Image (cartoon, rainbow over all chains, first blue to last red; front, side, top):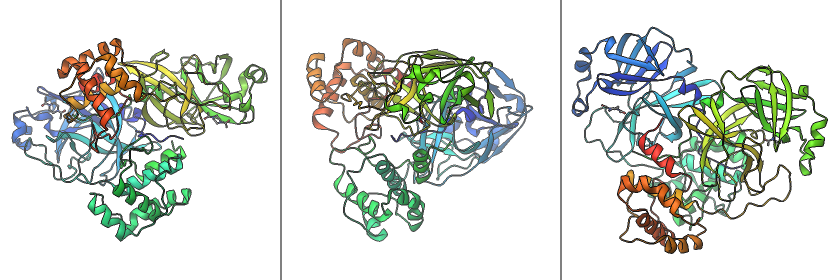
Length: 304
Length: 304
Ligand SMILES: *CC(=O)N1CCN(C(C)=O)CC1
Ligand SMILES: *CC(=O)N1CCN(C(C)=O)CC1
């Protein structure tokens, strides 16, 4: 019993973190096989970041300007290319600690672990979601860019996030491992506002199921609702519309608990309309939306 | 910017997790050098757990009854001993992945990471505190005992917790790595109630500092207080009494933010007396008490 915001074990990714230095800019790279992936802004001064022309900045850079250090051993860079907003540095040594891995571009509402790194050194691991506005609410200081987000399925690491940007509102933007930003963000120091932070309704319902499974049941009520009625309430409270797809995804938790998805929707509806009245659910005083249905099933069943 | 509940990277500990099986009981062991540490209740059936005599149960067990498996390779057990509530199994192979490590018995209020494991396989990592009642609020299913709690200082893992027990109230009890329970708990299936879950006042103040550092300042007020006055309010709200030691520990965060500890106490006092009025602090709707001052400094400075 007990339900906790849980990151994947980080060991497989710790073995991939390197330090990348270009001139006086140091940040993190991801070493998989004989390629090191890092944010292209490694080639910028802080001055450059106001309006960088990355293609033009990169022409002044050679293989030997990319200093790549794995712990205390330097890697030889034998090639470099820009793919969207990442650099790929070809090194002469395959990372012996390369796990089975994929690159996946996640959807908003999907959760992942972040291994926060500075100078290619892991500092900590926490769990995030891709917000509906394509920001993440991370913990990133200067030197943390090139830190990556990942899921693990048994032995395969799916890398979904590389850290690039803080918005002036203190939220985070980054790319998949093909260097494409999540959302409309750019690697430029300009006016970039996050859109509405909508709540991930399917994840809240997943977490309400988690609560029931672990004994927190005070918020169960005698009511039911419809997708259309619930969605009127979701609209009012900046919740993502609930779809039949979301209902289908909640089916297994529905089945295990014997609480119909639409009944749990009616519970959530009452929580939205009435607040928690100073009570808590799984030790939270607000509605948690960074557990996916898959996260709840994983944690509630003990998958490794 | 951003402040997140952050676990240590788990890689160094992942390399220490093994499966221990005795008869039909499987749980986790910790392999450091040529010793595997596991809960002594590995020798129990669920029936035994009502009133086990561990010394008597252990007499029926030989080295060859302790099946120890590191991934897919079996370790040869060449000796076994009971130390308090843990077994130490001597194996013929030093764990090649043994990190620099210490065994430390933490104090209530101290935080640590847990690598949740099943069958010697890591499932996830989350951050805990030793509660003032010597429980922890974990996420542990059957098969998770022998999972360990740890801090990392640069390269040295300090192991402080091994998981043993769920109380019927869904909170967790365990031992340090000398097999001594935190609090008055025993490895027996009996009536064991947790005492008062008091809030770790120094950790809440640490987290209020973290908030100010990261831009959440609405709860700062024009008031100050005294240790004695604050403690009257702490008493009323089941908060640990604040000591001069706690004030001294908050000094660096005091210094960095320029907010006197006693002024932040007065902010906390008003939060206790008035609640958050539907507002949030670092994305929480309650007062977080599982960041230590050391945790706030670590995360706010980017230590690795
Ligand atoms: C020095 C510099 O230009 N930096 C430091 C490394 N980063 C990040 C994003 O952490 C870029 C800015
Ligand atoms: C089968 C059995 O007796 N078990 C399973 C392993 N554990 C724990 C504590 O996870 C003990 C009970």
